Length: 150
Ligand SMILES: [Zn+2]
Image (cartoon, rainbow, N blue to C red; front, side, top):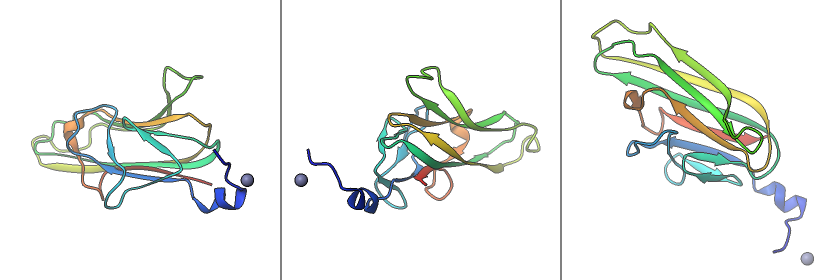
């Protein structure tokens, strides 16, 4: 019911830090958003997506820790994308790709980091995609997705 005065609106900071969730087969990725190192305040989480409720500038970031037991140079993409009524098709915001990154047969590991400033609108939905779910390690310190309002 009652609106929050801009002093009380501004005490509650708009922030998300979502951490890797190993027990999901989903794409886009699902995330931990309550316990451990995770944070969620003033932004909604649903089905792997961060759902913006206040229009404005935000810094958005994601790290993915890729690893495997036997290198075959399967290409590794990592993206942050958005869906809203203007881009019901998805808009890629940030993306990186690894090809020709390990020696064949060897145990391997490599991370990808994405971060940038975006102007987001209320009801924008933000997600993380990767090319090979099985080649992601989901420890909270290794694989993560977040943002904050500027
Ligand atoms: Zn009143």
